[PDB]
Amino acid sequence: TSWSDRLQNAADMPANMDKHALKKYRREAYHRVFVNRSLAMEKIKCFGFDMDYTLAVYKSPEYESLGFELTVERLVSIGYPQELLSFAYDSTFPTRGLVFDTLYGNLLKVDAYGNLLVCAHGFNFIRGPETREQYPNKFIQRDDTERFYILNTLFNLPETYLLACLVDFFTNCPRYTSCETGFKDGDLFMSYRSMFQDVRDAVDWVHYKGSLKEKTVENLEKYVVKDGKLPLLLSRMKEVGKVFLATNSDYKYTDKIMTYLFDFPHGPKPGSSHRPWQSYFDLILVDARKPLFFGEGTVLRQVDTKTGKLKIGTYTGPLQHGIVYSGGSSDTICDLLGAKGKDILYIGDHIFGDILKSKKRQGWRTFLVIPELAQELHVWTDKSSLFEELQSLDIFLAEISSIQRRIKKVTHDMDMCYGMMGSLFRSGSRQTLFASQVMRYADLYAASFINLLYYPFSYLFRAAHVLMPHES
Amino acid sequence: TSWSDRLQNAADMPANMDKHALKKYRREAYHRVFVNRSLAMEKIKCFGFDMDYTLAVYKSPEYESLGFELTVERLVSIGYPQELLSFAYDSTFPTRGLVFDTLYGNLLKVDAYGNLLVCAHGFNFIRGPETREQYPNKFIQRDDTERFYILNTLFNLPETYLLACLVDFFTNCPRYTSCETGFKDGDLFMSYRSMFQDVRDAVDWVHYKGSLKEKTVENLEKYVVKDGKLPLLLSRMKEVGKVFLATNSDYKYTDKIMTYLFDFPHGPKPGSSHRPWQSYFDLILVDARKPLFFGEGTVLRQVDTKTGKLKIGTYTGPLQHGIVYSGGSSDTICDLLGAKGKDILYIGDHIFGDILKSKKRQGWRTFLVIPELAQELHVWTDKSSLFEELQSLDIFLAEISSIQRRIKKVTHDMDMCYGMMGSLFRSGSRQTLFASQVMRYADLYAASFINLLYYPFSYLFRAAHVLMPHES
Amino acid sequence: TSWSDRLQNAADMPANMDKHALKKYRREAYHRVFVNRSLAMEKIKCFGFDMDYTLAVYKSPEYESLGFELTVERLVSIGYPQELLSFAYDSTFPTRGLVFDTLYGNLLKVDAYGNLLVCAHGFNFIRGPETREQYPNKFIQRDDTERFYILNTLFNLPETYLLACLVDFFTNCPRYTSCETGFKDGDLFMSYRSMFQDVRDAVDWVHYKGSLKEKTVENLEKYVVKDGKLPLLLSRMKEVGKVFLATNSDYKYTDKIMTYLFDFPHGPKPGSSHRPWQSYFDLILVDARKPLFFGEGTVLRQVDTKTGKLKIGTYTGPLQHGIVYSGGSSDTICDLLGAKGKDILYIGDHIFGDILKSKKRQGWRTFLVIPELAQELHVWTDKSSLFEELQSLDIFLAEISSIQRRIKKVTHDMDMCYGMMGSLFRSGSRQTLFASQVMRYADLYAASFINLLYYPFSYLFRAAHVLMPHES
Amino acid sequence: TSWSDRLQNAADMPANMDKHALKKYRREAYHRVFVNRSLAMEKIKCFGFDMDYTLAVYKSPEYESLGFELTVERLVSIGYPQELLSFAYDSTFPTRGLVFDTLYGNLLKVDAYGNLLVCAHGFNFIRGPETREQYPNKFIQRDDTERFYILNTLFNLPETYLLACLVDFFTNCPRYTSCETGFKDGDLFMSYRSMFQDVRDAVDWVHYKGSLKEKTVENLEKYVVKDGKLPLLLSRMKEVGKVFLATNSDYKYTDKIMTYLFDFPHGPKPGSSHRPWQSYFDLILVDARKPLFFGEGTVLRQVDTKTGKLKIGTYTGPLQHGIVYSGGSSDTICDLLGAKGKDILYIGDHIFGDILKSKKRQGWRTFLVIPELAQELHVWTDKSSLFEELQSLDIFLAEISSIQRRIKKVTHDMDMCYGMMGSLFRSGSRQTLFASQVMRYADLYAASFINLLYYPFSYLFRAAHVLMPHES
Ligand SMILES: [Mg+2]
Ligand SMILES: [Mg+2]
Ligand SMILES: [Mg+2]
Ligand SMILES: [Mg+2]
């Protein structure tokens, strides 16, 4: 049972708008909106949305497998060895937010300070002492973006596994000789970094020039979560404010996915006439190019919605009914909707491109969608005994070598419950980089944006005040 | 009574190394080491130091006044108007860590997200609604370092006040016409940004080509805190590990200041022979150029200690007794002392150049000295009733317009207790940028590095584990 | 009769290797190698070649028309107006080496100092006084590559004409309103600069993703000049030195074009067995990425000649029989062939990418192919009376208003003999930028590289010594 | 007899404005204006001047010796060895325009294409074969400004000699061990590049913070050429156009030098009242920061001429009588004087900063002052037999080993007549980089700007038309 199975289960449930039932529904962690910084919903004038893995959650592991398979085939068609075709996507290996080190070919799970929490070369997990040969301080400078690539999105799950597959394959195939920084086969040297670049290239290609989109759109029920409660939440948002879409995808893919997401024999609730997806938005903007969108952006263009092509020239007109924008910048949205940043709640899944950058560059309020949180919550409650235990050993240790080895033993047993790369949010008692960025930049977060439906629209989301150590 | 008065009071006290007295001395917040992240002192192999405002704490307000007066005189000598000479430094105005906005000429106190906490144009404090003309979202992008200058060090206290003085002067002198971005006097236009640059230039000049150093060294007792407990702590550090100095100052100024700091008729404790300051360090490095020091650094040079000049050429030799280094990089220290970053506790006062950058670029452990914390602690306890009260109003509000105006009333009354720009760490219930960077990058912090003397050298500094909202 | 008609006429002639006939053949300017700097052919160890418009000269105007037509269709398919389809390529308009000014939408012919020789907005030729509104000093800074694009290659001939077509079309179509920097149609503004970028984009697309290559290769006799004397010259070069190919084109296109260029029922001369084109080269390198090739280059790869794909990884082996390289740099050629720059004669048509950059960055000897020189020579002799006349008027003027207007009259009449944009090399008595770069960077130049066949291979090409004015 | 001796001889001669005497005076090459491109003097509306080595020609070798001696002393005071004090400036060694190679420590004389004409390591002249170890192609990429420094100005003459001195000293002093890229003395390594940087630093320091200016101004007759014909030429220029000064020097040095240059008991001619130097200029601009001046420039400031300090703020007013500008840009001059670039004749000595950059960036007409041309002309006529001979050997060679060795023999004998580094303009029959830049960017050139006095102010300076090889 995958995380998208939990989300699809909640999606099949109709909305009971009885206020008592609503309060009791955000009872369960699965349906709750979690709060990092207080947010007064009556001060929110505009609700903005990302599409992919926000409004349109791709089913797991079917969609990752599709991307993995088409990426492998692209690599084989440009000349990678045939044995790649016998790989098969395995969802229990990759955790999101890992760092690939293009120098040594390792996948790393790190904390906010770049300390190593897990190191895996292929499928071989390097333990503390052996990592010191390559990482003398058990630390990487995360901001060295020329060496380290952070696999931040659910789109990166297939290549996370594929990178491990490839390193494992070349390490153990006798045609190749392993070196510190890559593999040699006679007079051809393949560095982990050029191997990495071919994988990124092939993933991009499959999304943009290959057949991934076509195969998605040809079987949307297999690949995309559908929820009748989405029209309801959007129409309620429109009753108190403005609603906009700002997505990196192009207009033709956006129209196909969105049409499907609203494809019900009714509108906002059963019994009402169905309405086109565009009628739920005061502003629709595609080809956003986030995060650049939150700085200088690009030239504001206008989509010809009959053809799906951009009209020629820069659009200099006003907001008008029916218009669909391409490019522009976050200032386009503020001007056209008459909003200041703190009036805006932007809802997305990209911790960097949607959340970090809109917060830091523009002062937008932020809501981070974490689709895996559905399952992570299940594991966290179910095996809370393991963590509760672990908490106590570190306090026993505070007040010796026999303790530490069981610290490492239950850390391992706790982490294995999530997958081979452990929880998205921690390794034992150590929080990941990803968890720390959630806390720092996501004002609100939840397994699904739909959890906002279970809150009255004047609700004050409350977080506790932070105190420095000396202020306690 | 200034913050340096508190530190000078503690400095006059001899050390009682009775273990029971030591534990009871770190009783008081003034003498405590505060913990953001746990640190096991037995794992620390090297203790490293900054000099200025770390080992050598300049007395306040005498030293700020000296810098203010010499900066004003430099500005007048290059042609600023004579009325500047009637300014006098006023320590109750500036709080450290303010942002000067070179576009509109405002001093701003902001939180970690660049939201405005205080806005002052000259000595005129702009309240919420009027700030929206210039800051529509009550927010600045802190990383726009071309527009915003963060006044992060105690060296910036005089220019913080001077900037306010100048803006106030030109605003109210009838020879000048105020515009949005500066002042015009006939055919000469002075922008706030070029005004700002002249102030930075003049401060630099006074430190490097003017008479500030000479006047400091000519009356060290007037300007520099001296503490007989410093030799004692350093010699105890040398018993368990290595000790190094890495300072941006040059060798001649370093030798004059350090000689004074050790100028007692005894060595580590009363009764012992006095020893030169250099004997307390396994490695001495000047002209460090931090934070560049924590990246590529500069060429490693060797000081000729008889002349105070650099020897010609790059030093390629080994660490040897008596040698004094200039330039180099943090890797110089790791190689020469045989250390990894997490073996090192670096002790300094520059939140960016000493602490943030050594943590992020190198994984060093960090100890931040905050000299004002002496007084900030006094105010915080004394008027805790105000804050305790404020805490309760926000909870009353959580469960209306009459409440909010008293929220703003006690925020004001609390803040005025610290100075006109409020506490270094907060404005009411909102933490400053500076406070948030302390928590994020300073593993330990204290009013003085000397507070380490009151802890056994196997002490485990303990911080509580962090939990995400959904993990609670 | 086009310039490629002259070249095709000379190509149909078999070689008479009788030494007396050879000397009398380089009699005629059409068959001569012209000398800017002396070059001793016995000191040349390596002859290197470009392919497109050097070994493979595309027939004019058929090939330009094909490129024009496919570029127009691409523009229409992305949304430019239908009227574009009624354009037809006109070879009498464009001269090579014009500068497009993306700010004002003008085609400009300039001298070496950026002085205006001709200015055309669409098909409207702006005369001196009116150009001063937009060019106050009748001058452009050529190196402002963000504003000015120099149309340096014969590949740019179709877009040179197309740019003029488009500006003319939008200027005179009543649906659009002309502004200084572009055209507006209601709420869409098209700047000349974005119009320019769409044209560049469409030309690139047609060459790399469209059908230009396919349609070329499907009718090579229609589009490519073929000359039985090419195998002969290459085999003679191989008798005294080494021969290499370094081309920006990929391997599959290179193999198709080169196979055709050698497709004769004989080898070097009639009666000899035919040999594959690859046997004429000691080193074959594709995907050169010149001019970057003459600096850092790119990673050296190896072509799989059976599949036309690159082998995976960097090629680290030696030069070996049969190998085909991709990428690398000019140093690859020097190392693998054991050559220094002055040992190398590089033969190409790109005045910047082949000639200027190999000379300045590497000290290579250079031979510039100028296909239009065939016709330019014909016009220059035929109407030498006009130029001879013009020469005399400027001397009459040296020793008044009545003279100047006839100066401008015969300048016009001379220039019209070449085309609407005049000679490649001059406008009246003023040399173009292009002519000055030929003289400065092309050691040798000729209508065709084949003219080297008419010179013994110890020939000393001789240029006169240059004297400064004061040395005369 | 130095080149400044020739100029001082011509300067002592009073002006005979008899038109017949004027024509017969520009008879002699010493007094002629040489023409690279035709220039019609009646089209010149503004004459602009540089000061140093243009209006104010420093006497040779006295001034170079002064700069050499103060530079050596600065190097010794920062720690270079005492033996430097026994160096003495030797004017027969350095020729202007040499390239210092910071990697290998060689002085190089190169042509326009970066081919080696002379290579000297210290005082050791490397002949052809041995240079190939370090320069395999006998060529340098001149534009690699990180490795190569071109010593373009007469200010660089002392450091040209000093660099050779130092390399020679360290090579032959037994305390130091020579390596490929520098010198080692135990544990200190001095690279030629850091040695080079210390020399540049010391030259800058001596001009800007040392005592060079003071010692110049204290004995102007010893150091500066004075010519009573300068007021006369400037006043005649003012009769037909506008005159401006644009100099990099500051106002106080400019006023001292200019006052001296006009210090005669008369004005423009004997018998007329003396006038202040400022009255000869319609526009005076100091701190020009050329060549940046010809691009974005700097902020336009106004000099307070009573104090010599800049007024505070940007000057936004109009041109007015008495005003002195600081900074700004070339556009300041065009706007304030109502001129277009081709209306302007700019007169200076810096081939890059004055001539190349004003021509290429702005289309100004250019007049290059070459003070050494006085002596170079003398040598060129006197020993024309050597060159005339050399010309004939290369023609004998064109139509063998015995010839070449005498080619090299007379090249050497010709070059030695100029100095150890040969003529500024050539080595034998090969023109230098400097000569080629004179021809390309200096429309006019002369030993002194004063030679313009011998031409009527409607004179058409005439250069011959350039023809490409195929046009002959
Ligand atoms: Mg998304
Ligand atoms: Mg400090
Ligand atoms: Mg070509
Ligand atoms: Mg000068």
Image: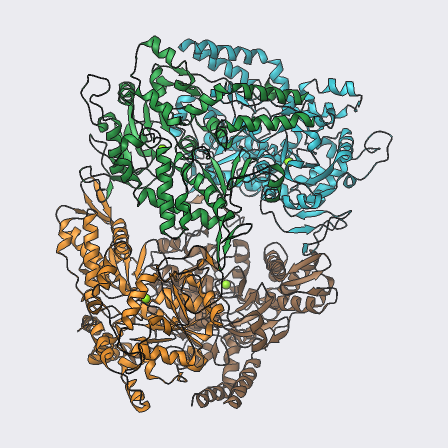
Chain colours: A green, B cyan, C orange, D brown
* Residue C330, quarter of the rendered image: bottom left
- Side (left or right) of A228 relative to D16: left
Question: Split into 4 quadrants, where in the image is the N terminus of chain A?
Answer: top left
Question: Split into 4 quadrants, where in the image is the C terminus of chain A?
Answer: top right
Q: Residue B451, percent across and down?
A: 70, 26
Looking at this view, is D362 or B262 the one in front? Answer: B262
Would you place residue B35 above or below residue D214 in this image?
above
Q: Residue A349, percent across and down?
A: 39, 30
Residue drawn at 45 percent across, 90 percent down: D396
Q: Does the image show residue B1?
A: no
Would you place residue B382 above or below residue A295 in this image?
above
Looking at this view, is A143 or C246 the one in front? Answer: C246
- Side (left or right) of B347 relative to A284: right
Would you place residue A246 above or below residue A470 in this image?
below
Q: How many marks?
A: 0
Looking at this view, is A4 or D392 the one in front? Answer: A4
Residue drawn at 65 percent across, 70 percent down: D89
Q: Does the image show residue B315?
A: yes
- Side (left or right) of C245 relative to C134: right
Looking at this view, is C286 or B234 the one in front? Answer: C286
* Residue D239, quarter of the rendered image: bottom left
Q: Residue B110, percent across and down?
A: 49, 27
Residue drawn at 24 percent across, 79 percent down: C10
Would you place residue D388 above or below residue A454 in this image?
below
Q: Residue D79, percent across and down?
A: 71, 57
